[PDB]
Image 1 (cartoon, rainbow, N blue to C red):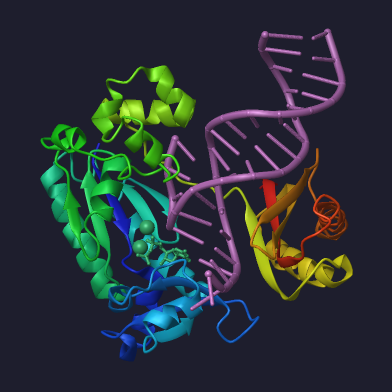
Image 2 (image 1 turned 90 degrees about the vertical axis):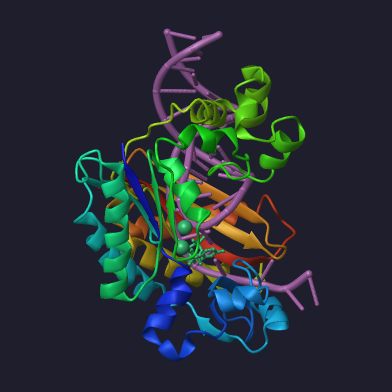
Length: 343
DNA sequence: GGCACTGATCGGGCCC
DNA sequence: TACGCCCTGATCAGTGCC
Ligand SMILES: [Ca+2]
Ligand SMILES: [Ca+2]
């Protein structure tokens, strides 16, 4: 198998540069503002100029503004980045036997037949793909070329930005012989530090570690994964991916326990959730983030589909029950998720 | 015990 | 210190049932 992983450098920020080229070459920060205050919100992404100054994704806006006061701080415009993504994935689809859009930001392309098994022509094709995306969309990306999904991802993320990582089948075993656990996709930090500390620094340290004592720490799934992965027996095929849930989340104007206050926001969240869902959900979940950013959720799955008018009533009840089991804390953010969807 | 099903938690930008 | 919006599957806990 010959897999080409595609990963769009500093995506949101870079789209903001394509739309406003005055922003290029200077620190730019793409923020999600909640509307509580002028600065309340979070860093979605930043160009590398801003990252040099210490701006990191996930960080509060005000905190980025401490270390990078002169950066350009722009609000996130997800619909546009979505459109950009769509067009780019469409470009990719024409090159692959199969494409797996892992998300708005990245995708895997099985090019095996396309390049007729010739891995080198696979690399060349990857160059053509980078070139084409650059020509048409003015977006730079990083590419991984490898004999599987995971390796392609790993060599990609090790090559950012604007990179072209390659792991020829010749080199695979050597790459696995010297690969840290924290460098594996799907292994946490809570999980990484355990393995790392409690014996298993690198991947090969799994081939010789009584399977069970590993299964204790990771679980059956992850242990099986890491095992076949280390054994060079991971092969997972490229599969078209199907959305399983849609959620909409709102920051309330002010913290409160009063359902009567939260409800119109919860309804609003329900409305554009349903407005965007592609089917009927069998399960509705209410998500409430508390003052201290603790997350409570209460959901209900039905034997049938849930209409929107019904969702209002169900969700109100679920919310009322969340605030029966907490009794003390105020809600800061309200959210709703539609799951188990019938297309 | 073990099936079939519901339900809560979780991590990080996606993955098993 | 500071603090958004959004999405998976695994895993474990509970219930009812044969
Ligand atoms: Ca990515
Ligand atoms: Ca990216």
